[PDB]
Length: 137
Length: 102
View 1 (cartoon, rainbow over the protein chains, first blue to last red):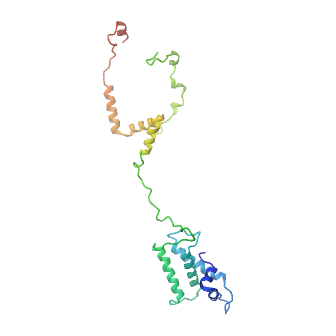
View 2: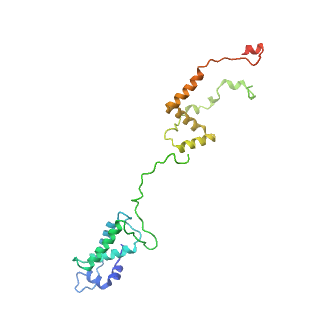
View 3: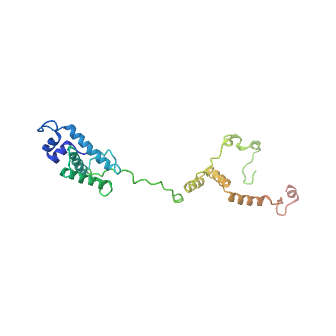
């Protein structure tokens, strides 16, 4: 859960979330929590797809850039039909580009609140090191 | 008495000293040469310096057994002595009794 309904409302205003989330009432009246939850879950799943090879999956903290990316992807997911030239689609593409840059080691995952994220041990591995005759015998 | 002057008692000569130590005769060598590294060898030598000669003795036995060149050299050196003729001589300007004892 890198973003919440509060984050979506704050980033896109409550009116737009209501309009793109209420599918049964015309005009919209309330925000459907289930739809928003599914959209946020899908955004988190995509982000994990991008970040699985460099960091641990169950992150204990959410970096701020991760919050922005999740909010953007979740909003893009709340559109049933999304055309290519829709600006929301372009924002989603830019965020996906940021994610790909992070995955390819060109961008670093920033601070969460004060501490660093937790990189995986992929680079750590070395055989073991056999150096007998060099132990001050 | 002996050469060192320690009192000698003929009572203790009837049985070997180690007879009352039947535990020793049942022991088996631990073979410390297998899996030996320079650190292990240094520890073995240092411990031997401090009075733990068991590990050092077993290591020496393994070393003798596992090296053909060293074993050949030691065997040749010892066989050199084993082939020497020997004799018992009386002390300097010994007397008739000393000559008979010799």
